Length: 195
RNA sequence: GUUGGGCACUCUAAGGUGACUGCCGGUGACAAACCGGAGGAAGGUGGGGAUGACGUCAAAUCAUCAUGCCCCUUAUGACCU
Image (cartoon, rainbow, N blue to C red):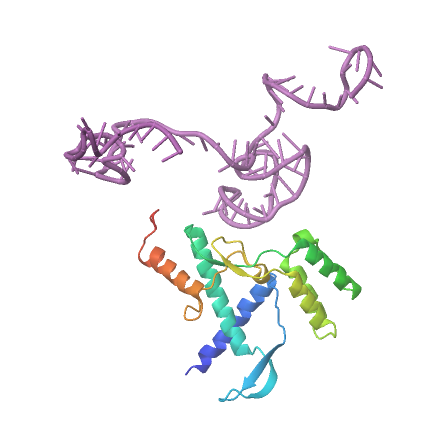
């Protein structure tokens, strides 16, 4: 009974992913380790963490929910919490652009006005190359860390203007705050100056 | 800097230019906003500074005001070492 829904979920996730990549999001697909332990905490193995179709599908659904909530509250113009990723440091990024030129990769843009899509075009060009891992690593080191902020400053890595965390309030206090602000402003209608 | 000297550059004292997110767009209600993008000595409150109608609250404080209610009065007074 669920198989038809799962096939529609896969198609929708692909449509959302295609849109996200066309918007110029940076797909940072790095090989992470997963340490496997037993019930006694003894190490059994160290494997590559793979992101499957099912994880990527849920990722796209949580992303579009997160974007939709952030955009809604941005236009409501009430105090809210955002998940921001600021523009890269122009000096670090200039050094990265000089670095990838040594491998013969030429990027369209200047370090002070780079579009995320221009970085994604490098990742796509280095995919399945020996130099992939290192170009990827030096690109990451040129980016800023994402953080929580009351200002909607956008999310460079996701190439979006509106982003918040809404989808995990059991394990993230920002999401729990987002839920309280939703209840305060939308459900209870409490948009008064003192609130 | 002496020794002149209008003393340019000082300097000092005004006066006056001066900056306005104004220009100018990316987004978007061709909106806002924000990203800006230039000019410029300097930027978005050019930056720090700056503002009453009914003033008003056992605010705060009986050393605010109270003497409160004190009191000692050749002494709950001053002078000396």
